[PDB]
Image (cartoon, rainbow over all chains, first blue to last red; front, side):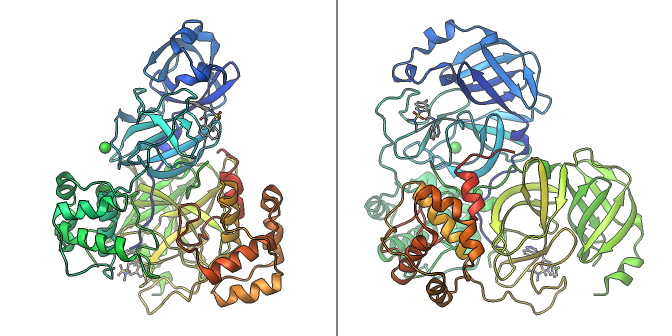
Length: 305
Length: 298
Ligand SMILES: CCN(C)S(=O)(=O)N1Cc2ccc(Cl)cc2[C@H](C(=O)Nc2cncc3ccccc23)C1
Ligand SMILES: CCN(C)S(=O)(=O)N1Cc2ccc(Cl)cc2[C@H](C(=O)Nc2cncc3ccccc23)C1
Ligand SMILES: [Cl-]
């Protein structure tokens, strides 16, 4: 019993964190095999950030301008290349702690663990989600650039995010491990703001099914809804549209609890209308949207209370 | 910017998790040097005469895909210590520490000696933890990291009827009035950790959330009278002293913030949130707030 925001064990990622220095800038890098991956803005000054020509800045650098530190050991850079917004530094030593890994690009609503680092040293681990507006609500200070997001289903680490910047509202923007940004964001200090955010509907539904599995049903009602009528109501509360894919994905939780997806949608419509009235759901007074259907099946028991 | 429930990096603890099987029971063990520590209920009462029947070869210890040979066994309170033939080469610098209610720690939840998740939690004033555990999680451990030294503070033993959890320090002494056996036992009425809510209000101010600040101040005595009525723990002068750094950083005296807490308790939040929460959060200590709003590394 119990339901917590749970992150993956971070050990396989800790053994990959290194410090990357270029002139006055110091940030974090991900050391996998003989390559160190880091944000390309490590080559910029604060002035360069308004309109950086990364290609012009990189061509002026040589291998020995990049200082890479792994623990108390200096690594030797023997090559360098840019791939989108990531810099790939070829080093002379392969990381003996390299785990089994993949680079995966995620979709909004997907969750992942973040290992927040400063000076190539891990300081904390937390769980978060890719928001529908492509930002993440993280906890990052200056020096955290290069910190990574990952999932560890089985013993394979799937790297999905690398931290690049903080937007004016305090939210964060970054790239997949191939250097492609999530969202319309650029690694430029330009006037850019996160779009209006929405609630991840399929995740709130999954979390309501987790509450039913843990023995709570106070929020259920005798009604059902069509998918269209649910979306017409949900859009009015800034909830993401629920698609037929979302309904199919919730199938296993629906069969386990005995409650149809469209009946759970009717409870959601009612919670949005009435609020919680002094009650909580899994120790929360708000509707939680940072647990996917997959996270709920992984964390919760296979036997409903 | 941002404020998350953050756990310590779990790697130094992952390298210590093993699976212990004895009879039909399988649970987790902590392998440090040549000793495996696990809940004594794995032998399952009078544990000493139940233990005397067992031989070293009855305890099956598995570290990854490698079998560890048990060469000795002894009990210390509610923990079983299995002497093994091999010292753990991944043993970190460590201490066994007993924590107080209100203190926080990270839990590495494991099943079959394999870590599956890490989360942050607090020792409740009623000595239970609101964790997330299924059958097979027994032996999972709680810890803090103070530089490069892991301080082990908790070992999971059982789930109570309300879904909350009970366990021991690494010397086998339970937190709370619990016993390791199937009997009628329940968690006492819980209270809110006042010094932790105050720390979290200071974190909200640091992150630019000031709607709850007011011009008023209060006395420690008047605040405690009010707090006792909302099932909040008494605030002591030690708590006030501990909040000193956050008081100087934000410019809000601890009794000035206590008056904000008083108004929140009597009026509610009125449709507003603080750090994305509609409830007053009590699982961040003053040190957690200073650490997360400063970037301390391990
Ligand atoms: C607050 C962000 N700035 C305006 S900044 O510090 O001047 N700035 C501009 C900037 C622009 C583009 C890119 Cl790709 C990176 C950056 C840098 C940046 O975003 N780094 C930070 C990252 N994460 C959390 C951060 C919290 C605090 C400070 C800095 C953080 C550096
Ligand atoms: C619900 C607890 N039971 C009644 S039990 O499963 O029959 N039971 C009895 C019992 C008695 C004493 C002691 Cl020290 C341990 C236990 C066991 C126990 O607490 N294990 C569990 C631990 N954590 C989460 C658990 C979730 C689900 C089940 C079991 C969990 C095992
Ligand atoms: Cl995805």
